[PDB]
Amino acid sequence: SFIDVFNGIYGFATGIQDIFNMIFGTDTGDLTLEEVLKNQELLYDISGKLEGISGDLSEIIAQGNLNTELAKELLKIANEQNNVLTDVNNKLNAINSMLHIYLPKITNMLSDVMKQNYALSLQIEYLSKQLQEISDKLDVINLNVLINCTCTEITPAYQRIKYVNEKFDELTLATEKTLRAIANDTLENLTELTELAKSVTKNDMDSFEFYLHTFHDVLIGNNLFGRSALKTAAELITKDEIKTSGSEIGKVYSFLIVLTCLQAKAFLTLTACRKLLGLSDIDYTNILNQHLNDEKNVFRDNILPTLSNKFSNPNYVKTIGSDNYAKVILEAEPGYALVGFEIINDRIPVLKAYKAKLKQNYQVDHQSLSEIVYLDIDKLFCPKNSEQKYYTKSLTFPDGYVITKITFEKKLNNLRYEATANFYDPSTGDIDLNEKQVESTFLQADYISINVSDDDGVYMPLGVISETFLSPINSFELEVDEKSKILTLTCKSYLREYLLESDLINKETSLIAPPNVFISNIVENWNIEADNLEPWVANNKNAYVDSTGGIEGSKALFTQGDGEFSQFIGDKLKPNTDYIIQYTVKGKPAIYLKNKNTGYTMYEDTNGSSEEFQTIAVNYTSETDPSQTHLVFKSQSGYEAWGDNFIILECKAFETPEGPELIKFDDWISFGTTYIRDDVLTIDPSRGGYFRQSLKLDSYSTYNLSFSFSGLWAKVIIKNSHGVVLFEKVSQQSSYVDISESFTTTSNKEGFFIELTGDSRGGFGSFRDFSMKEKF
């Protein structure tokens, strides 16, 4: 569903409890497996000896004469001995039947435990990736003092727990594979797993339970000698700067989740091993819940309030942008809020802004999660061959406000951005539309100037600008250093409140990891991993799906000859809308967008050769309401092609506005002696007279004005009644001279007027060709 929703530590504990209840449902009887085997071997030895004795008695009783009374007595003794032997054999057969019905139940329980454990562990894969990224980005060269304080007491217990969990998973997988591919062979297959169960369930000193308890003890710091591992790990992570996704809250929470889920898996392994041996069922639900609650309380009361909810971009990429107008609007619909952003630079830089509804206590609703994709984000943050001025401000809003719309405007290399935040009322989760605040830099005067200097491109932010889990933001800003030409997108999240109200008090939790996959792409099964592909269809067997001929291990579509892969996507293709077509290909492929009836190639590659996989991203437009258009991927007629990651994003972009004509011809006001004839406004000097016309000039705006000069010393002044003059020109050789200069209005947005008068007593001036347009 493209969304990896995380159910929280409480959800993981609830899943572990469910697996515990499933384990306890399997009744293994009243005898330990070791006791059953001991009884079986004892009865087997006794039965063998008695069989030998009975055979000897039978072979010595059927040989001699044995008289009459002696024969009867020996027959009676043999009958009694055979009765004893049959009783022993009946007991042995009962033991064998009990074992033969006990083993399949154990194997089924182990398979179910492995399946549910894998299902639960699928949630923490993202958190493990985040922790690995934090570790890689950690500046361990000077932080060895702290890293040897946290991983000095937790290391033995951590190693034991990880080894036990991994070995249990490996052995369970091996047993499942063996069973998929009777009692004696089952025991021979499960001997290693039973040995592991005996090792972990041995109620002895320095047992698995001992390390399980000391793990929690080191995490909390019950002993006065030691220090809490969670607190020192949080200090290690939060200190200095770790340029990864999410804030300090998210990183420390991910570390806590990793440790908590490790403990939960360890307890699950212990319970499964206890059930495997047939030991007494002791419910570890209470102790596991106690450990998890203690750790969450420590994190909530001694770590979380001191953490910062500020997250920046993961890294930077040195790029050269562009110039001229560039407007992006990260607007969210009423009832929605922005929860994160992502800047990806693989083929064409893109900006993904995630917007979603809220479900009380700053909870992001995965049902309504959507994204907006903006193309060419590099042209907005960086210049090409000029100097760009950034008007930056920390657009911080009061607590309780959620940012809905963020607007960036780059006009004449003046990057001014504004944000709007609506009231949230977390008690009900209703984003009020009437109550809102606007924090804008459109009227700022101070700026930071950066010169591109050709190859010295600006470091555009790159990566996921979001918390470890999607959450509303109440503060957004762009930071410019002006020394190394580094731009940083810095935001403040609301994850602390949702953690305090959902997961740290043992309630329902729904955390959404920032998707690494475009969730708004209309190509169903964009990457071919799902089996029984319904959208993808092959015209014949010429083209198939290679399970390893793609990116990493992706099952890429391989085309060889006339075969091709078609997918009908005409239903989701909106008319008159820009789209981004991106795909990773190998060889010489060809991608078309057919329209079923009257087959025409709206988009076509028909070329492109590469011995390795490369990513191609292009722009596309659908104009005449297709409503029937299928993507077709096909190799060259004499070549082999591989294709994967076919994504068609409904992009949004803004062009350069034309700009309204501020000055006109029919609204000229005239005072004194002025003669208006056709396209000529003769102004009479000496005699008191002048032409004027009000203007709608904006703030910090540059306007190009065309003019036709005539008449000696024809004064032109674009000014205000207060005495502020922005554009003044005097004609010197006024035969047919024309001027098309430009003027900038910094901050005096009002009814500016252009006055046309004369300096010389004579020289009847004539004016025409009026056109004042804002430049972008």
Image: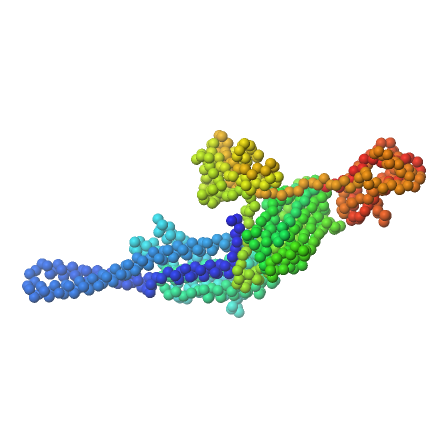
Q: Position of residue 273 (x, y in %)?
A: 39, 60
In which image quadrant can residue 428 be found?
bottom right
From this viewpoint, is residue 160 visible? no
**Image quadrant occupied by the C terminus:** top right
50 relative position to 171: left or right: left
Residue in the foreground of this view, choosing between 252 and 242:
252
Q: Position of residue 195 (x, y in %)?
A: 36, 59
| In-front residue for pair 671/502 | 671
**Considering only vertical position in the picture, is 242 above or below 382?**
below
Image position of 100 (left or right of 672)? left
Q: Is residue 114 visible?
A: yes
Name the residue rendered at 67%, 41% in the picture. 655
- Residue drawn at x 57%, y 62% is 501
Horizontal and vertical percent position of residue 640: 48, 34
Q: Between residues 471 and 382, which one lies in front from this camera angle?
A: 471
Residue at x 44% of width, y 34% of height: 540
Q: Position of residue 20 (x, y in %)?
A: 42, 61
